[PDB]
Image (spheres, rainbow, N blue to C red):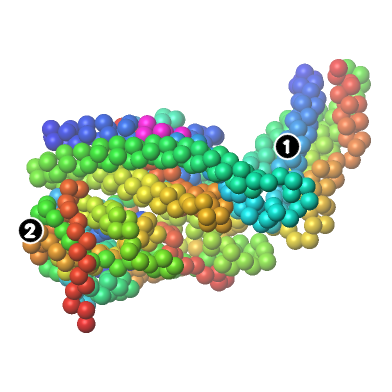
Amino acid sequence: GTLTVTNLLEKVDDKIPKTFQNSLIHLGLNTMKSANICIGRPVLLTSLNGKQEVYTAWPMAGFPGGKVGLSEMAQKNVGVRPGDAIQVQPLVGAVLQAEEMDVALSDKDMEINEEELTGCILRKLDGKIVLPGNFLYCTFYGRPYKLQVLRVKGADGMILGAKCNTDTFYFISSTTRVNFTE
Amino acid sequence: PLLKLLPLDARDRGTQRCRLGPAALHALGARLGSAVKISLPDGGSCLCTAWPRRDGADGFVQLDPLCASPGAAVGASRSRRSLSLNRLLLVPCPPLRRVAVWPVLRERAGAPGARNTAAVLEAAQELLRNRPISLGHVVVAPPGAPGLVAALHIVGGTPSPDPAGLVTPRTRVSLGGEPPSEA
Amino acid sequence: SARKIKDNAADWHNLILKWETLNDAGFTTANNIANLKISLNEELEKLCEELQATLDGLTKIQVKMEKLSSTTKGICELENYPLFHTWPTTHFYEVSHKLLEMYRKELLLKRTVAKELAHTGDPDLTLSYLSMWLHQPYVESDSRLHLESMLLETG
Amino acid sequence: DRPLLAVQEALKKCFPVVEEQQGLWQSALRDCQPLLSSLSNLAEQLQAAQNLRFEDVPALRAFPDLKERLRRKQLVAGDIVLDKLGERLAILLKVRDMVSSHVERVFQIYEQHADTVGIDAVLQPSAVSPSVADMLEWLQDIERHYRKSYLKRKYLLSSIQWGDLANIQALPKAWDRISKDEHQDLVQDILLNVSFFL
């Protein structure tokens, strides 16, 4: 339940799936086992400041235990830095499909391309479980972006915008619709 | 108990199977890939194949109406209605020596006539592989399926497939061709 | 001490060289993107991705030379309480600071031209952008001279 | 216990077959591209040899009995290509039958044992291996993918008739489409997710 944040392996050693190109947190088989963390499953990250985010574990046989490489954007969202400690929890609760999601731009204020963007968000993130108020990262034709989760509507008629390891969650699939309101 | 009916994400939506949480799987005790006669709450039963929930979750049931009841197909989607467990049933499945069908054809508009029966027969024999079907049911074809066939209204079943029956790779498929009870 | 300074000089040299090389590769990439755009999907996407990779190599270079700058400033301060050929050795920090500022603003401009190159309208923007990429319009030529001069004082 | 070892052996015995067969499928597919391109080209030529008359053009006029003596060559040089394609497709057919037989073997073993193994024991993931249930599911999905791909390939390729010289000139696109519509590299990701054999 306790682990030391680090940085992942630099090269994307192509022993990696493709529905997982993003939202990975490398681990070690030993530290995989020491917390009941099963391949391809999701898992929860709790910050020492009270922030949370969920990611798809992956047991890539690199660095040893105690260390759990993340992504830079993950470290931003969690708001931590190398060496620091973090809480890991094997997700156990339900996981449903997320119908409606509403996010607002970080005010890049590009010429707004409302539907043009969703076509890349979905094709670039299907699988990333979300939470109220996080940051995403598409790259629609080279340029960057940065969004902000405001509300999600879950097909089991529920609404968010999700703090303990045994609750609902939601993820984006090719049927989720999104709106862009400040 | 009582079960919600979520929509169905794409992957399953293709094939036949219906997902389910290990609670109800333990309830009716079917190992896997079994048949489950499901009675929609809108009239007209349905038949699907069992497969466990992805994340050991509970009390939810996603299903896909491939082996439907005639016309009652779309009644399976677009809802939030419950589904009581008693509305599901485990059904025995025999190997169903020989079968017999009446197919619609896909609107390959531009060349009807004498329909090269070898073609339609091969395509149908394909679409019926290893599926369990129960007499008196449509079997739609999945989207973008190959070939010509687009329906297999089920009529002739040799060992009386009234509950249901498994079509095996060694089963004659007589393209009988008798549209039944059209009203 | 001064040994570190001489190392800083040689590193400046090799770093700028690698910079130019990567800029060449990126310019080829951007040519490909502009042409592929003018001709009319995912191919373009792989293109933009490896271009971004080029940018990341650039950023790596930038952070290395920034560390160079920092160490130089540190030795500058530590020499409080004179060299091969009698330079102030503050002059050194001045040099490295001008270099750093130039190259960093350059990196920013490259980042913007990447950020915009994909979806551009009228072609004249596209030519001007390819230009901005190639001519590096934030590197006053005397820079090389400067470096050379400094590089001269340590073999 | 022993049943679980049975299905486990069955599974990580079936997978390497799937890997090698996928490699063969892939290579055999890659040969088809240039052949099909050349066939589109021959189609284009033969298309542009009916838009003339050859009885009224100054030079060729002194050459009686040419239009025929040309066609009856282009057609041969096409027919040889098309038989090469037929050979490739025979390779494809071999691979689908191989995979289907093996997958059915796996399921049959499972059905032979799935009464003395609580599905909960079937369905629980470990630290170095996905759930048995997910393994069988992926096997079934591979078999269905191979079948549909093969059969759609054939009902595309066996609709070629010298005589519809427009359709025959669109193959290289309809083919590529038929390839770029399955899920991206299934066998690849399945092979990865099972790399840690168990």
* Rendered image quadrant of residue A152: bottom left
Specify few, some or many for label 1: CA neighbours under 10 Å numbering under 14, 14-19, or 20 or more: few
Residue denoted by label 1: C25
Chain of the residue under the numbered disc 1 shown in the image = C
Report the span colored magenta.
D20-27
Q: Is residue D4 left or right of residue D36?
A: left
Quadrant in the picture for residue A15:
top left
Residue where numbered disc 2 is placed: B159
Q: Look at 17% across and 61% down and name the residue there.
A: B100
Verify whether residue D71 appears in magenta: no
Q: Amino acid at mark 1?
A: Ala
Local crowd size for mark 2, using a 10 Å CA cut-off: few (<14), some (14–19), many (≥20): few
Residue D44 x/y as whole percent: 62, 50
Q: Nearer the viewer, residue A110 or D117?
A: D117
Element assignment for label 2: loop
Q: Which quadrant holds the C terminus of chain D?
A: top left
* Direction bottom: furthest residue: B183
User: Regarding mark 1 in the picture, which secondary structure is present there?
Assistant: helix
Q: Are marks 2 and 1 in contact (CB under 8 Å)?
A: no
Could you tell me residue B108's position as x and y percent? 41, 65
* CA distance separating discs 2 and 1: 71 Å
**Amino acid residing under circle 2:** Pro
Looking at the figure, which quarter contains the N terminus of chain D?
top left
Using the image as rendered, state which of residue C141 and residue D157 is in the foreground: D157
- Tell me which residue sits at (22%, 34%) in the image: D10
Given the image, what chain letter belongs to the residue carrying mark 2?
A: B
Q: Is residue D89 left or right of residue D109?
A: right
- Residue at image location 52% in from the left, 55% down from the top: D163
